[PDB]
Image (cartoon, rainbow, N blue to C red; front, top):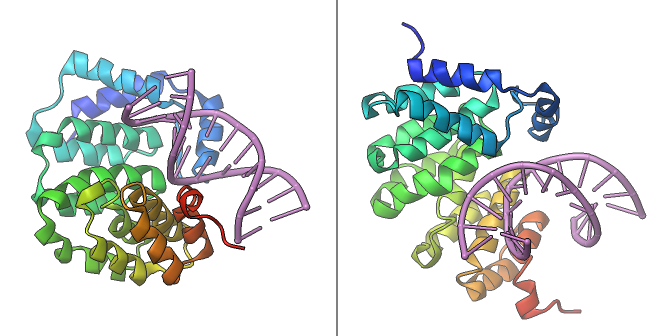
Length: 231
DNA sequence: CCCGAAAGTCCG
DNA sequence: CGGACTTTCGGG
């Protein structure tokens, strides 16, 4: 079965505009986990737009197929493009897609893909269907996969006044002992972000509960100005 | 334009 | 450890 023609067209068009000179530092920035073509976001977005203009966006029946096929290509720009395409199908994504999104999180995993899946796509789903959180979050925390653990921490990132504080702090308590940078930093980020909505609750939490030094320092990067640094 | 964010390197 | 500094990206 041939590659979907839309994916083949995107592959051809991106490859024709590759930049091996830029690809080297781009690959180093992601710790050489991926090959890169060397195409930065503004041009990558335009090249995708070119292909949509010529071919049209595929029928929604092929949405998941297109994403998978791009996910399977070696160069990282294809995963970035896949996420751009998934946004174009946003109004068609619902709670039945949680396993599909899980599988994206745990394949070709790094912060650049996971952070573009979790607080947006998964965040929106669990905001509408909070009763499903307990069908996934406990498994994610218990798993050996750090990207699922990060997903558990960051899916509420943008919730603001809709943050479930008890849940957030429970999740952080489960993961506070992790020695993994991407977990410590995710804890820092979600606390720093939530502190923009409720600084008193974040300050009290970090002063009275154990956290890795990195997590605490990142959490209070801004709000330490509001409370002061005691001698 | 601006700022804040993931990251990243380099240094003490 | 954590501060100083870097580019790239998203949003105001």
